[PDB]
Image (cartoon, rainbow over all chains, first blue to last red):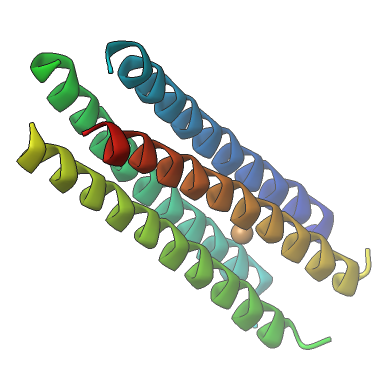
Length: 39
Length: 39
Length: 39
Length: 39
Ligand SMILES: [Cu+2]
């Protein structure tokens, strides 16, 4: 068990979460455009 | 305290967060369908 | 530095993130009700 | 590898995720205002 690897694994997991939330942000931007042009 | 267990616990916590965000994504897809057919 | 404390701190941080995402989920449920009755 | 640094790095990563989710919350508040005045 290399603590350094553990740190790299955790950072990789946090990066994945970040990207997921970012795609959720884009879906909300998408919705807001849908409404902004229709309404 | 087994560092390996600590790593498995952290990975399990990150997996749970991922699934939670995924369900939030599905709720937004749901909303976007609601509006897309009504509007 | 007690690895056990480190684990409890991390779990507490993940719990806080979970609750935050949960409140975001509730805001989306709120929006979906707003639209579902108006539309 | 200083376990303390590892802890500070993890806390910094969790803080970044928190702020990201917070900005997503603000985008949803923004959308809800858009609809609340138009509808
Ligand atoms: Cu984490």
